Image: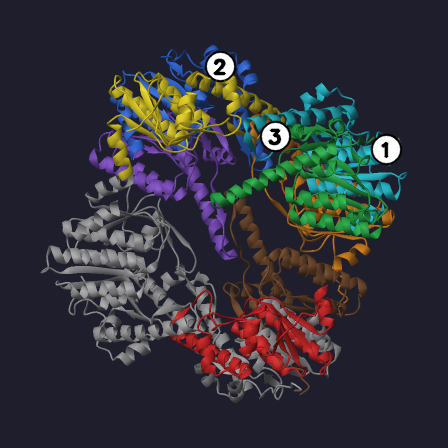
Chain colours: B red, D brown, E orange, F cyan, G green, I purple, J blue, K yellow
């Protein structure tokens, strides 16, 4: 497979891609790649390129904890669009190495979900939603430096940022030009 | 057909899942029967496996609103919204056949309501409100504390006709009238 | 059937999602009833989970246009277009049953409108116009400033019958008329 | 039903997408009403989201052909073929309700017409002819130059009832007739 | 309904694709109308986007066969089989509305006829026969040489009402009869 | 409707594919018409693209069985089972319109009959029997030797009205009765 | 329609696959006709390609049970359950048209009955019982030993009208009654 | 896979293809190839052959930023048809090495999209459309040298260019003949 | 994959196949193969075997320009059927090396397409059809030597040629016998 | 793939299979194999085993011309069933090396097709049918030695031959026993 | 593929499997394997293991003739179930090496088929059925030693044999125990 050939050559250069909706398949593949790269050489950086329409929160947390706990620094790049969990994982890179490319778009929005069970089960599902919402906003606040109150207000509806606006906001540290 | 004859005898047959369209038909029938004769009783036969809560409260208010007493007779089964409507009949005229089955349980969804977490906070709040209102209504008509009903309806609670009598959902169990 | 009898009593039953076909039927009924007797009142029963905005304004103008007063009674629920139409009844004759539920929210699409960005600029402008018109209409009939309504309808706002009274959507909550 | 009563009052209700079958029904109604009474007016109520051009011209010629004046009243919306038919009513009797919406736009296809390039040259020529004829017809009935209409209808142009009056599609906006 | 009234006025409305079932209905109507009154005229209104050739010749022979003159009026459009049937009306009584569209083209298949080459030789021979017969019939009724028609119908040829008059398909274009 | 009127005139309209249900309806009509008046003629109009053989023989025997003469008129086309039934009418009263098309061909299957070879030996034997019976029946009514018909029907043989006369399927080709 | 007229003449038309619903309709008709006149004969016309065994025995017992003689006439074909019912008519009044086809064969399943081997032992035993009962019934009405029938019905056995007479399924083959 | 065998042999010659509707799969594969080629040799050119019916704008921006930031010059070739994002990426090659082949077709048109949410969400989606429209036209103006006003007017409806017309317009620098 | 094994062995012998409806997948694969073969050895011929029911015009133009601009001569063979773009690409081979096999069939017909948009968009689509029609006929005239008027008349409806008739007409230079 | 492994090993022994309905995929694969085998060694025979329910005529002509023009003799074997284009290609082998296996079945029948267009297009399609019918019968007559009149009469409806009857008729030269 | 790995290792040991409904795909794969094995070593046995629910007769004849004509002896084993063409091919092994395993089942039944055409075509199809029926029964009689009359009577409906009953009947020569 040509696509895999290219990606594997880049994996040997410590470059990994998040190229689709974050689900469990992507999260598990990507966590495996981070574990493997850190095992091969824990001193060298990993460069994670993000281009994603969004994804599941649990899968995103798998990726995020693997990134945080990896002994190596992980740099992140926003190319194309980094939406909601792409944005989270972008801002989740090590501070000082979070990059946006000049014509990237970064989208922040409150979580989506759904309600399925009996009134009792729905009370439980709603409680868990409340917890998730607070935790995701807390982590965005830690990433960007914005007050959590501002994250909650801004993420109410789709909030689009250009690379420049993302730099001022605090999602990224640098915008790459050349 | 048999149903038009029953209607001419002031009989409503609640024989379907209480959907929104079904609730509309039932309410139309109750309104028409009240108009025709406000003093003479209305009899509602109940045999239904289920229904929605919003439709339940629609029918419930129409039943309490009309001037005529409503006699409720459970044939077969009265499940969830049919069970509340059975309890909601005029006191002293709520009846069931000997092998009638009454099923009471908390309201539930089917499918999935999707949206932003902020929309689902509201939807979950409304569903909890609907549960509270169901339990309060049954308490008003059965004499059991709403807390007891809230516990009882946690899981499908199936009552026999006799148990439905002891539990306050019906006033009496019908005796067979066979002449021989 | 029950609906033809209700019509003979000058009663319109708005029991369906207010689609375009539904709006056509409602407007035809209003026009016929006005023709039959311009002075005697028309009663519209409202029990509907939703409807479109274009259909909403069609019915709304027909309701304001006809000579006869329109009494609006909310059974079950009046949601989004049914809610506006409930508010749009003749002042002093807008009523709801005790457990009636009124749901007001900004208009929304389903599916997707696709086209060139230049077409979608126009479609988005028209949808914003529809939101503005909905909020203005409710302000005219509820007495709340259109800005307050614009904020309130941002998310599904569910009112109880009593709250619908306090909020200006209905004039009174119906008492039960049971003789016993 | 309400529609048969409206017909007995010489009222045609153009409440559907103006397909070919719909155009056939409308033309049959116009022909029958002319036969019944050539002198008394016909009223056509318009509430429709769209329709085809060929059906449009069918109805248009039948409307101009019959001896009786045709009064056209826009309820809800008059879109594309309904808009032309609204303009095509008898001068002085083209009316709309206050919140009526009028949508005029160039004719369009749906799906795909496939064939040899030589067949598609002909089909494209016919579609350009249909656009020209639509714009010419509106010019005849609105008083605007066909060139202005050709520019205006390039993109969906939505007119309010008042704008439809100023733009020459209707003669007047109906006042509400509520007695109170 | 409008169509039964039109029939009582000896009016046939050819408003559908001329399928086999449609041809059966049209022929039944023609036969019944001839039986009711052999001397009084029959009027056939034509508004149809197409039809098959076998159905075309069925209707054509029934139209020529009945004793009563048949007046043919094109509303909207007369396409392919409707166009031949328009031409096939009684001379002097073939008429069209000003914006009526007449479309004549060689007969065609849809889908695929499959079989052995020896079966398809026969099917192709029959289809060529059908083309020849269509062109000959139009020549008989339009006055154009069948060779000219054979060339003209090679590609979709669309005629305006005036062109249909000049081309020999109709005898006159109807003037509008509006009293005002 | 037109068909009930035709029936009241003792006219059967064989306008559909002669399926089993269709054959049942035709036989019921023939039986009823014989009961109503055994002496007065029955006219059967034939316009059908095909049918099955078993249904063919059902109708054929009912047609020969009833006391009343059966006049058969081919409109449009008489294909395969309709063609045999056209030939099967009362001698001297088998007629067709000038452009009527008659199609005779050996019987055939559609889909697949599956089973053991021993079952398919029987099914193939029965199908050969059906072919033999079709050809024998046509020989009885056309005057051609069954061997000639067996050869002619090998491939779709299409006859014009005049050829159907010369070939012995009809007695005469109808002249047009137009008064002018 | 023709079938209601036939019923008024005490004629049942067994024109469909003898499913369970079909058997219910036939039995209802037989019961009603017996009630109307126990002494006057009932005629059952048979034209059906098949049916189930359970439905067969339902109809069979109803036919033997009613007081009125039942005349059975085979039109078209009598296959499997229709064949048994043809044999089951009143002796001396079982008749068929000259080209009527009678098909007798052992009962069979369609689809698959699934279950545990212990359930399928029972189902297979019941199916063998049904075969035995079919063959015994035919022996009772045809005069052939049940063993001979058991062998004959192993494979589809198709009888002509004359063979059906010689084989004991019908009493006579109908002569054509054409007056000319 | 034979197709991949051919493409990989050409990848080793620094030739890469954009052969379908630009979506995230193509954009990510192509960005990976550009990164990889630039890593192998940052001094040599990359030759990008474009034959595409159109594509998504976010994916196209991923490709475009990767092209711009790559340390190596990227030449572009219009073969078959370069429509809307094929056209953008064609004109986005380094100036002086943007080629059209003699019978190529280049199609310029305004963006497409769709509207899905509540009136509030739709106001947001429409605002973002306005921003995207302006940015895409600005970049086309930078590429071709035409005034942005002309880009907006011309792109109103499908505007077809032949290779010669594209050369005069400014999409390409040269038309290859031989 | 056995099919690919055979095709790749033949690719090493500078033999390439156009074996299906010309679409973008085939055109891109085939253009890549021609580029690759010309890169490996620009002096040796490429033998293109054509057996195709037809195809898209844009894809066919990609193939055609790649053929014309390749520095090496390209010979073409008509086996089975060469219909409409198979015929075009057959006649598009270098003059003197366009072959038909004895029982080949060559089908010439005017382009097919479709009309989808609003009256304005349809006017545009029809204009582009007119342009395409003229260009395709012009190129067929250049290939065969027939007047463009004759190409337009003959291609009105399906015009079938046998190999002998194709030789007389001018689609091919030789018919191979042995 | 095991199936391909077996087939490729046999390809190296100059044995090739026609194992399905002849369509363009099979015809192109098989033509490629014949070209390749002839290129590897033009003096040695190719053994073509035929087991096919039928197929398209154009695809069959591609195969047939490739067989005829290959510089090497091609032997053919009828195993299982050789129906209509299997039969044609069987009889199309070099005379003296066309084999049937003892329990093979050979089916000859006139071509099938279909009619789709307008009356004018249908006249054209019917004319082309007539031409094809005559050519297929002419070639069968050349193969078997039967008069063309007999081929046309016999092929009117499905005409089944056993291996012995096929030998007497002239489809094959030998029946293999052992 | 693991399944193929196992099967290929066994192919090198001259063991081949008939593991599904006999159709043209299986028959062609299996004929290719027999040809290949016989070519590699024509003196050594081939062991064919049969486990099949049934299959097509033409495909089965391809297999059967390949078995008969192969220069090497072919042994057959009945494992699981050998139904109708599995049974035929089981009994078709060389006499003296046809084995059943102790709990195998062997099913003999008359052929199945279907009737599709016009009365004329159906007469032809029925004639060909009669021929096939007689030939299949003749070959079963040759295999087992039973009179053809008995084969026809027994195969009227599904006739199940246990391994012991199959040994007495004559389908197999030995039952393997160990």
Q: Which numbered tag is attached to residue B5?
A: none
Which residue shows up at 38% across the image and 40% down it?
A: I60
Numbered disc 3: what chain? G
Q: CA distance from mark 1 to mark 3?
A: 37 Å
Residue J82 at least partly seen:
yes
Relative placement, left or right, of E30 versus E115 is right
Do the CB atoms of the residues marked 1 and 3 lie less than 8 Å apart?
Answer: no
Q: Which residue is mark 2?
A: J141
Q: Nearer the viewer, residue K8 or K76?
A: K76
Residue found farthest to the right = F39
Give the image location of residue D47, x and y in percent: 62, 68
Mark 1 crowd level (few <14, some 14–19, many ≥20, 10 Å Cα): few
Q: Which numbered tag is attached to residue G154?
A: 3
Give the image location of residue E122, x and y in percent: 62, 28
Q: CA distance from mark 2 to mark 3?
A: 48 Å
Q: CA distance from mark 2 to mark 1?
A: 59 Å
Residue F51 at least partly seen:
no
Do the CB atoms of the residues marked 2 and 1 lie less than 8 Å apart?
Answer: no
Q: Which residue is mark 1?
A: G177
Numbered disc 2: what chain? J
Residue found farthest to the front = B180
Quadrant in which the C terminus of chain B appears = bottom right
Q: Nearer the viewer, residue J23 or I112?
A: J23
Q: Helix, strand or loop at disc 2?
A: helix
């Amino acid at each position: 497979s040509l696509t895999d050939s290219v990606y594997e050559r880049l994996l040997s250069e410590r470059i990994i891609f998040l190229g689709s909706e974050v689900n469990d398949e992507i999260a598990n593949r990507l966590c495996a790649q981070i574990l493997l790269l850190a095992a091969e050489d824990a001193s060298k950086d990993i460069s994670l390129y993000i281009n994603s329409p969004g994804g599941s929160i649990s899968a995103g947390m798998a990726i995020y904890d693997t990134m945080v706990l990896a002994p190596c620094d992980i740099a992140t790049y926003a190319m194309g669009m980094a939406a909601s969990m792409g944005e989270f994982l972008l801002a989740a890179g090590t501070k000082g190495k979070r990059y946006a490319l000049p014509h990237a778009r970064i989208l922040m929005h409150q979580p989506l979900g759904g309600v399925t069970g009996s009134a009792a089960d729905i009370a439980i599902q709603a409680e868990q939603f409340a917890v998730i919402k607070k935790e995701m906003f807390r982590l965005n606040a830690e990433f960007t430096g914005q007050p959590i109150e501002r994250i909650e207000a801004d993420s109410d509806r789709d909030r689009w940022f250009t690379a420049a606006e993302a730099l001022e906001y605090g999602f990224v540290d640098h915008i790459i030009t050349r | 057909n048999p149903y038009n004859k029953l209607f001419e005898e002031r009989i409503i047959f609640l024989g379907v899942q209480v959907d929104d369209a079904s609730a509309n038909d039932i309410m139309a029938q109750l309104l028409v029967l009240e108009s025709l004769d406000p003093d003479r009783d209305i009899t509602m036969y109940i045999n239904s496996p289920g229904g929605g809560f919003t439709s339940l409260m629609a029918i419930y208010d129409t039943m309490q609103y009309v001037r005529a007493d409503i006699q409720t007779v459970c044939l077969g089964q009265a499940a969830s919204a049919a069970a509340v409507l059975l309890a909601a009949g005029t006191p002293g005229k709520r009846m069931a056949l000997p092998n009638a089955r009454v099923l009471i349980h908390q309201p539930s969804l089917s499918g999935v309501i999707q949206g932003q977490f902020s929309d689902l906070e509201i939807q979950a709040a409304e569903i909890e409100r609907m549960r509270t209102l169901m339990e309060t209504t049954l308490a008003r008509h059965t004499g059991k504390d709403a807390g007891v009903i809230r516990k009882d309806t946690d899981r499908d609670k199936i009552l026999t006709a006799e148990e439905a009598k002891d539990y306050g959902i019906i006033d009496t169990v019908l005796e067979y009238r066979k002449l021989s």
